[PDB]
Amino acid sequence: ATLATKKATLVAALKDLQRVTVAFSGGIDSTLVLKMALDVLGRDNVTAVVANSELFTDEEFDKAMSLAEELGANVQGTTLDYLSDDHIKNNTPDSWYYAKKMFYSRLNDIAANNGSAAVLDGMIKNKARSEAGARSLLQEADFFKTDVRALAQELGLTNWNKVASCSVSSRFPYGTTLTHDNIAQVMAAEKYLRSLGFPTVRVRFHNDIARIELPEARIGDFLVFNDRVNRQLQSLGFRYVTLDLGGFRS
Amino acid sequence: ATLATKKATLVAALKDLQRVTVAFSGGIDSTLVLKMALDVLGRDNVTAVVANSELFTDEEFDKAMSLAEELGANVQGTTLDYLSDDHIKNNTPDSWYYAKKMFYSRLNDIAANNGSAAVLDGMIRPGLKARSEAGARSLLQEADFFKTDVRALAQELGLTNWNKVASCSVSSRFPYGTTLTHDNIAQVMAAEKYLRSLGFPTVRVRFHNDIARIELPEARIGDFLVFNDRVNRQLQSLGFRYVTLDLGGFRSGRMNDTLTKAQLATFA
Amino acid sequence: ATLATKKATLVAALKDLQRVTVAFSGGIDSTLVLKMALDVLGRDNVTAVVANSELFTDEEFDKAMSLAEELGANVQGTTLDYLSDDHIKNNTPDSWYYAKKMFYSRLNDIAANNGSAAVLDGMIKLKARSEAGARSLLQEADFFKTDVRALAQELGLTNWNKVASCSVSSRFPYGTTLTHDNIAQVMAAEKYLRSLGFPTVRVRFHNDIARIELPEARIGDFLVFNDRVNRQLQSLGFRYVTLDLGGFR
Amino acid sequence: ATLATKKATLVAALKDLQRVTVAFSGGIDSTLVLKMALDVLGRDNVTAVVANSELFTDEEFDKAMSLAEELGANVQGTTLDYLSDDHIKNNTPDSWYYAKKMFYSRLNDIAANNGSAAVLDGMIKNEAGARSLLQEADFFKTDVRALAQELGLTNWNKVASCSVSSRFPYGTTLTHDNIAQVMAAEKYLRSLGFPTVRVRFHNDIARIELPEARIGDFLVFNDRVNRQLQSLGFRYVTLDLGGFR
Amino acid sequence: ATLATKKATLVAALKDLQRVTVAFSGGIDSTLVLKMALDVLGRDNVTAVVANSELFTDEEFDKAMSLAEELGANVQGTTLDYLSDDHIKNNTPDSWYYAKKMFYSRLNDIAANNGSAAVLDGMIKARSLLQEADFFKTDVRALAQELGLTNWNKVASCSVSSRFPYGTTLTHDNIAQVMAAEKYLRSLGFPTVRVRFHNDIARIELPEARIGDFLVFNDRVNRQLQSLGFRYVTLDLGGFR
Amino acid sequence: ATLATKKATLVAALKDLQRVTVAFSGGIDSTLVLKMALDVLGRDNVTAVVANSELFTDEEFDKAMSLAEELGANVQGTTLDYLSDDHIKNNTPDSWYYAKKMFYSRLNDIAANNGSAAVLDGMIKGARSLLQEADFFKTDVRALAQELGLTNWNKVASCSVSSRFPYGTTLTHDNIAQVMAAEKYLRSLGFPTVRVRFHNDIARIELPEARIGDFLVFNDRVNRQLQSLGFRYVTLDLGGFRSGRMNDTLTKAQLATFAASWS
Ligand SMILES: [Mn+2]
Ligand SMILES: [Mn+2]
């Protein structure tokens, strides 16, 4: 019920596993997992893995790989071809599942190859991981968001990814087929908009229409960029560039 | 040559044809032809026809017909079912031609029954011109009238009231290949009438299935922000899932600079 | 007097002159003069003249010429070279005087050539107008601005140029020398700004700095154009393109 | 039927009355009546009356009287004391009645004294002592405009005029000072480029109603409006988020 | 003047007091104090108290009480009835004084009851030890992070009495009405906001730099504050202050 | 390669020098250098030098000096008379060089008298830029600044007031005070990043383009205020602050041709 007992449960489970592979996103959860694993098992018994794929930006991958090295961990990139699975490529509502199944499947192959006893992720108390058998040790020790921040301060952890990102599949309607070209064009559009000073942004894909979602409090500030955004996204392949009057997550 | 002769040749053609049916749009050109026909032939010798259809607003039709009654013509309304022609219902790039063909066909059938010698229009292809195939005569075109000569002579005859903004068929708000229905046509026109009621007379609601794409003059987009939320829910209640505003505005590219206008033209 | 007497005095003056040339700007004063001339002497005895020059836009020139033709007049354009006079080219406070000297001179020559007895303008109740023998008939009949609009409504006149036009010299400080290139630079800049939906606009010239004056109530509407205006006006030759926070004048 | 029929009915009605007094506000409706009255009967059979009062602006009064002479009428101004009636000074919901009663009473006395057969006002489609010939001829807002261009009328007051009583809550007493306070505020707002505006009076709070399409253009004036209306006596100067009406 | 000398000055003062009761707001100042007392004196000698009242938001109360447990302290909520004092209920210009009188009296009682030597608060440049150690806004951030502090309440609040004119009677309903209005405005993306109460008129103060960003919310803010009971919803052209 | 190696090479270079004088601006680069020198060499082997001149605001000087002693360094102020040099006083295009030569000359003199082996500055990828020798980029500076708990630094990059005057215009106390009073007023309204370029009777305000919409509510007071400081016209540059950096690919290249038109 106290953070000390919850931290005791986490140290004991890690001592039990002896050698672990950690699915590392750069967030505060996996940062806490990978830092506790290094402290109890040592650097040669922990492998931090960062997933690289089309569905996430090449820049966020670089960020996660540096944060793992800053913790003092051996970090390893693995490249996933999500588009090879037809459920992910045709963006059915179960795409989230086959993406997560192919992710944990690759984590088990490297953990088999490195002699680890488990795959660890950063899920707390607030379907594919349990199918493959990954362990959420923070969830098993009854960590909540407050306990993660509490133990992170106890250990001196201050640096992590404060915004967590979503799969780029969210910018496509169900049934639309994802290609190498329309994924890349959606991400260039969002990287350009972020470059203008709009960190929270979405470019929803509707074939020849780009549908830009912004926080409504920023749309007044956005007017001075209308024409540059319009022609920049047309040079990326959109025929029409539009702004959704509903705002962010209409 | 000079305006006195151009009006003289126009009167000579009208005197020769003796009884005419005039395609009347409410514009200044068709207002000038029908009033000159009245002055030369008198009321029982001229029939003004105003076309009603789903492709144009109920407000334009009521207005064009009142403006013809105000000039003193015997006026007749006709309703055209443009959607019966598959070129118009499937919005082919040439559906403008098949629209005008069905229009002049109905006008010629009206002119056959009222005993007029010609159909006159207010003019200042996949085959033969819709006029030349139907027998219609553009008498201002045979008299070499220009936009100013129409305006010059329209005052000379005391003409003051006409439809000044001109219209565009509602088919222009749909992409080529999209099928026009009674429900989605009503949907765009309700959307544009609501936007107009907010104070934006020049507006377009382009139909993109579940996306509505609003074109406004870019100079009004700053003024438009206070209506964003009401516009979005109003057009969602009209059936659109997403309501969006095109960042190029109305007539994308006409108000850009030399280099960036050439870039906006290359992308099309 | 009453507006009936003032129109009676105006018709008698025109009837006596029999053949006339009218300097036509498109404004309500010259429109009322040229329509009274058409009605009293007929289209064949009245010639409307519209001045074209480097100091005024081709767009204001085109409007006056359609309007004169739309009133049922035979209208003729003339191009004036104001910059040949150095009083205009070095932009002294008497520049408008020497400009008007050259304007009425060309008008006098047209009236000799077509057999007119006087040149008429639309000035109501000045030094250069007199030395050329020009007649201001609305002023001779004691027309005021209220008499001008009153008779303009009696004649069914509804369409005229509402924006009096200013010579481009006002966009340069006193003493700055006007050239063909910097005159062309200001007018291209202003033609572009007006095309965006700002009819009331000025681009003040400060060598490499352009200073845009807009009505303060329109500055919010302008924000969406910042980037295109800035690059268009640099391609016209300005190094810096700026917006005056004081607004128009 | 057609505007020609509507104009004929109005011409025949005017010929029947022979002598008329016209209540002239300067708007397009009364401008169209007063010019038709002049056009059918001539300057000497028509009397244009312009009401001066504390409930309407001095700028509107001067404009209508100048517009009447420019239309060719003999025009005369009559002053009304709306605040002398206790129903108007205490701003009851029935204040309109006693204002209209007082207004038409004064017009009837001017028309009796000059021998006119009726008092005419500029009321259209959508008061016994006054005839509304445009409403009797079934003129609509569109038909008024239509015939106004047919006659070359271009100059009138383009924004509808409303009594200043609407800027005070029902039950508030009207004074010379608070009326002057609202009017100075609305006159200043109009000078910045907002013809349609209201300054609702709430004692120490001013509540400005603008057309919602103009509120974005208004931001550049926030600061100057806030100090001008404070020097007129408001402690708080505010902008109503509902807009005009 | 070295953050090391200032923290040493602070560590020395805490050791002298032994047992302490800390007035905890959830801000970085009171967060830096409450942890520093725990680090030098231990959990069993430090009690963090978080005040509950109608003059401050339920969210600020709930947030500070969790954030203090997250620091590893024994935390205790106390409820204050500020409206029981007639100066506070009638919102007199000196009512700020009587409000702080009830606050520090209740803390002092608590500190007497648990055997603490002083009540400490988080006031920078009762005992303000951060103020006695010459901490500045920047010295607090440097040392907080030093111990690993990242989580606190950055939006410092003010008593809701400031939204009512002097002499206006505070009720439970109009206090609830102003705070519902401000929570809605904050949720749209305007953290600094005031809804001044003028009976049937709401007068919104926003930072003038945000008024342009605010325009798109005019209509729903207008209908939202009316459904809360205002007849007129307005925006003050002078802005915040 | 790895941030640890870059911090490792940085620790090795500092250990060899033994005593250093640090040119301290208050920015993140020199703040990271000055702490790292303290951590390897101690308070008695590091002297932080902060330059005060007429060309920078009294406020950035005050902030830099508090940040140097607050990091635990013994810091000393040095005052440079940049306006005594004619290249700077007449603002020739090479003024920056003569400013930096006069700056580094005084730093060499202080390091001679306190027995330091080198003067260190904060320039990244006889002064030595240890961050540049350790292959630090903007990204490695921010990462290692977070690794050491450094939170406070001069966040809005600071620049010489000479940049607000055209080349050839002579700087005076009256026109410098005029530019800095104008810029200090704009900052108080909520625009930390701002430039008021001087053009004789014209002030030309550059703002980040993302703030220009927010600026409209201040148009008139900014106009009145800067006229009372001596400007006849107060204008807003439509290209904004650092024009071109946030435009599209074609527009950024055109504005770069326009910028290279002048020299
Ligand atoms: Mn903003
Ligand atoms: Mn506007």
Image (cartoon, coloured by chain):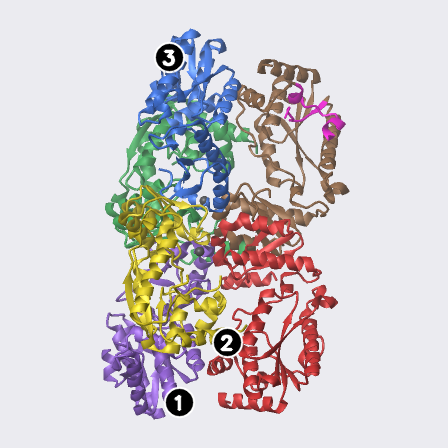
Chain colours: A brown, B red, C purple, D yellow, E blue, F green
Which subunit holds the residue at mark 3? E
The residue range painted magenta reads A118-140
Task: Between label 1 and label 2, give the one nearer the viewer.
Answer: 2
Q: Which residue is mark 2?
A: D4
Measured as percent of width and height from the top left, residue C64 is found at 40, 77
Q: Which residue is mark 3?
A: E13
Q: Is residue E145 toward the left or the right of residue B115 in the image?
A: left
**2 and 3 marks on the same chain:** no
How far apart are the alpha carbons under marks 1 and 2? 30 Å
Say few, some or many: other residues with alpha carbon within 10 Å of mark 1 (under 14 / 14 to 19 / 20 or more): some
The numbered dot on residue B87 is: none
**3 and 1 marks on the same chain:** no
Q: Is residue B238 toward the left or the right of residue D110 in the image?
A: right
Task: Between label 3 and label 1, give the one nearer the viewer.
Answer: 1
Which subunit holds the residue at mark 2? D
Q: Amino acid at mark 3?
A: Ala
Write the residue at 29% across / 49% down: D181
> Which quadrant, please, contains the N terminus of chain F?
top right
Is residue A139 one of those drawn in magenta? yes
Q: Which residue is mark 1?
A: C42
How far apart are the alpha carbons under marks 3 and 1? 107 Å
The one of F202 and F77 positioned closer to us in this rendering: F202
Q: Secondary structure at mark 2?
A: helix
Write the residue at 30% across / 50% down: D179
Q: Amino acid at mark 2?
A: Ala
The part of the image, by quadrant, that contains residue E96 is top left
Q: Report if the beta carbon of the residue with label 2 is closer than 8 angstroms to ligand 2.
A: no
